[PDB]
Amino acid sequence: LGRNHVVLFQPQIPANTGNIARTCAATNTSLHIIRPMGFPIDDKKMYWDLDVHFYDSLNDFMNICSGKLHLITKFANKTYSDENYDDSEHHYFLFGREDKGLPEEFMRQHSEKALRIPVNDQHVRSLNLSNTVCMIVYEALRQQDFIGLELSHT
Amino acid sequence: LGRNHVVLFQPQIPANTGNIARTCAATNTSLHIIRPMGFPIDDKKMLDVHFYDSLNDFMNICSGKLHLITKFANKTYSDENYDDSEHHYFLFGREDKGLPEEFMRQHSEKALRIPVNDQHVRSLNLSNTVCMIVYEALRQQDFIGLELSHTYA
């Protein structure tokens, strides 16, 4: 049964990853992480540890990914909200590192899958990563009539 | 000329306010803050920004459509229509306490929620909520506010 998935490539900032986990828990979104993370996992610093999967590499995730993949990038020639999420597919939303983005070779192979969040680049060139995850996940939900919210048990 | 505005009621967490400022700068969104903030402004720790002594002072100066972002509104943020030429003000409560009790009741017809499944968490992070609410307005407005930096200035 089709659902939404967030895929973080080598997440570098702890606070962004904790906010993403919270958005995933709130939305019944699965979380996928490509190792290595840029930070140590500190038990004490931290409670609902949601559907989480780890992968050694992008290639590793790609052998196991089944459905529609969307690359979130700065320079895609398509806007996030113009993609159609209103189907029964699994949707995977892949986000680059805060500092480096996604590998440029991967972006090239998959360029037709890339979507951007438009910004005016006058003062800042980018939005905070966890902010982008939340809005991308909720745009998919919006088009899906928020049905993922109702389907925790299933 | 119609613009989007973010209004923060007594924001309490510095990292939230710094992220909101970034979103505002990226989107040509004006930022309004009801004093007092829960944290000191530290210049070494480091945009159209306005400050207000109180919700009342903001309400005397507010002109356009006001939307209260709350947990329990009987309307979904994305079902409000933002596709007009009005100023849209999006008012967000404190991270810890939300919006005042009496204000919410007085303005309950203006309230919108972001639906969540409350099984594991009851809320989303404040700055995440600002960013999505602003971009939902932009989406309905065909992203036009991105193009009007100089005109708004």
Image: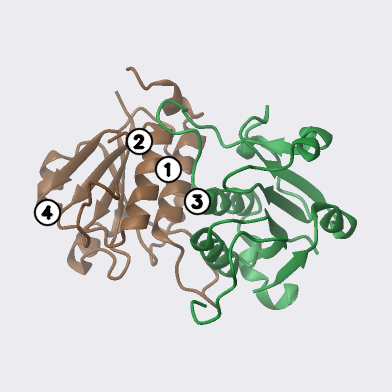
Chain colours: A brown, B green
Residue A82 seen = no
* Residue at 71%, 62% in the rendered image: B32
What chain is tagged by disc 2? A
Mark 2 or mark 1, earlier in chain: 2
**Viewport quadrant of the C terminus of chain B:** bottom right
**Viewport quadrant of the N terminus of chain B:** bottom right
What chain is tagged by disc 4? A
Choose between A76 and B135: the one closer to the eye.
B135
Q: Are marks 2 and 1 in contact (CB under 8 Å)?
A: yes
Q: Are marks 1 and 4 in contact (CB under 8 Å)?
A: no
Label 4 SS:
loop
Crowd tier of the residue under label 1, counting other residues whose Cα lies within 10 Å: few below 14, some 14–19, many 20 or above: many
Q: Badge 2 is on which residue?
A: A29
Q: Amino acid at mark 1?
A: Val
**Marks 2 and 4, Cα distance to the nearest angstrom?**
21 Å
Label 3 SS:
helix
Q: Are marks 2 and 4 in contact (CB under 8 Å)?
A: no
**Marks 1 and 4, Cα distance to the nearest angstrom?**
23 Å
Image spot of residue A43 (x, y percent) = 22, 46
Q: Amino acid at mark 4?
A: Ser
* Residue at 79%, 55% in the rendered image: B85
Q: Amino acid at mark 3?
A: Asn
